Amino acid sequence: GIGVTQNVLYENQKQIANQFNKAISQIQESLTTTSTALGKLQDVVNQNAQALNTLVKQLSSNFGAISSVLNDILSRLDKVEAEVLGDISGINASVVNIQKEIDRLNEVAKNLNESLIDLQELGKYE
Amino acid sequence: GIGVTQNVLYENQKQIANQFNKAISQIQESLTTTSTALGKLQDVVNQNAQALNTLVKQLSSNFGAISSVLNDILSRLDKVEAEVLGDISGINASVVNIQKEIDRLNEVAKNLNESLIDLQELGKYE
Amino acid sequence: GIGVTQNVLYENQKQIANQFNKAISQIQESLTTTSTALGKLQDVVNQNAQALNTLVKQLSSNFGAISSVLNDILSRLDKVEAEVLGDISGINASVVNIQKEIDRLNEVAKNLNESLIDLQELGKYE
Ligand SMILES: [Cl-]
Ligand SMILES: [Cl-]
């Protein structure tokens, strides 16, 4: 009463501003951390996708060859005894593309600097 | 002193409210972006999991068959010459289920609209 | 005018503080949710990586063996008729490590409790 109300409000503002700005920084860090983590997942997921496809590609080739050789062999035996397998090329791994979301997270982190609070200070309390 | 303290506090409130609301919108965007990115990762990861399992399934079948045919062949040769391989069915890819976390991110984004600040305006300064 | 300005400012502060604190809690929840989701993705992605590698390992072994057996067979036939395949060991799935980002998200969530606003109350309005 004696003259504190005006002073408590200002102190409250300084806290509000300090706590908010503190939180923003924490949030920016979390965003960058999420984008970084999302980016690593994308790399691994895609590299593993391409590994699986590269494999299917070779395997298909192998079974085509194996079935061919066994056929030749069986054939010979026939002649000798006379004288005397599913393809997997369709299996495909897809890749993910979240680069746009990753870039968006970094932009938002950078832009939160524009949402910080620059409290007008009252000398009479500073 | 002349009569500004009451006016600086209000201006500070308008900034606090404008900057916070601005940040909330930015954060909502980041959440939706994260959920969208998480959702795409889940789809690809699971589709690649199922591709790998579908493959193991066929491959096991193939090696069972190949070993069988080679055995028959070797057998014949025996008769002809007389007259004259690990299974992989156990390899399994697991799938992930983060749908609940994805839905939770979208709900939080929607609910932050309920955390916006509607500052009571003082006509004497408006 | 009669004496409300001082009272509207305080009411505005209570709202600012209530809405911010409410948002912080919402954000903490979103962070924990993101970390939990990121953690599940890491587990599945890595487990699927290791499954793919375990498979390549066995497959390479299988084709080495198959080519060997077919060679022996073809060889015999030669003798009998006389008397009468790419390796994939190089395909490798990589694993991801975002544990550090996951732990960082949880720390930030825990630390936001230190960014909450504890508004100094003015009895004259309470
Ligand atoms: Cl305020
Ligand atoms: Cl994967």
Image (cartoon, coloured by chain):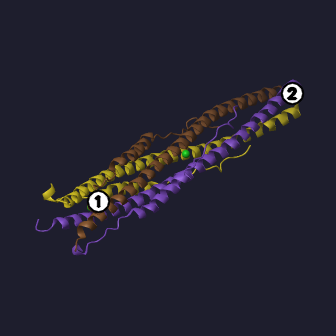
Chain colours: A purple, B brown, C yellow
Which residue occupies the extreme left position in the image? A2
The answer to whether any part of residue B84 appears in the image is no
Q: Nearer the viewer, residue A62 or B52?
A: B52
Q: Position of residue C89 (x, y in %)?
A: 65, 48
Q: Position of residue C90 (x, y in %)?
A: 65, 51
Element on which disc 2 rests: helix
Q: Is residue A126 left or right of residue B56?
A: left
Residue matched to label 2: A79
Q: Position of residue A102 (x, y in %)?
A: 51, 54
Q: Position of residue A59 (x, y in %)?
A: 69, 41
Q: Residue at x 80, y 37 (%)?
A: C74
Q: Which mark is residue B48?
A: none
* The N terminus of chain C, quarter of image: bottom left
Please determine if labels 1 and 2 lie on a single subunit.
no
The correct choice, above or below, for B50 with respect to A54 in the image is above
The chain to which mark 2 is attached is A
